[PDB]
Image 1 (cartoon, rainbow, N blue to C red):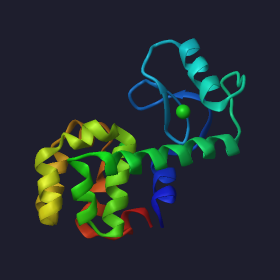
Image 2: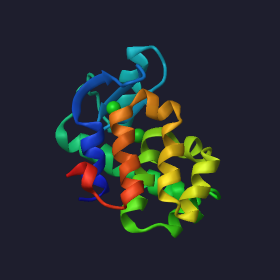
Image 3: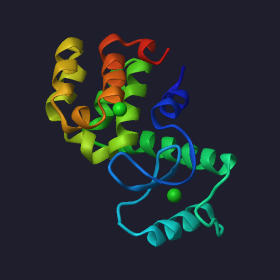
Image 4: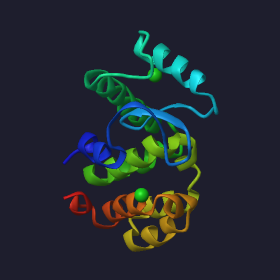
Length: 162
Ligand SMILES: [Cl-]
Ligand SMILES: [Cl-]
């Protein structure tokens, strides 16, 4: 298991523009296109991202390119972030993947905001962090996914994914 395989399970793969869990236009492997209510606006962002007239449809290869870019960006975002970087550096490889996952899903800012959990992560208080993370909109909206991520932090293993 690795971050790519982990996120592909969590996000799935869609080749046609679709609406995410929040109602936003997305495509491929969790690639958010836009928060705006317009499909056209979505189609424009998509063509701009792909570099061609897609007509709201991409290929597998293209979906994977988006995904590579997004993972890379999440990692880079963590490392450039004052609050995130140190947490990240303090963690083992499996737990780093869980943090990347969260960043990928809710962006650097959102995560950077879980002050208390960040402190617990750093202090390696596994069980308390798991409790704390569940008290969130995030857990309430996408519970199965959150549970997988939480177990990952709690145990430091890939069990929830195997
Ligand atoms: Cl893009
Ligand atoms: Cl879910």
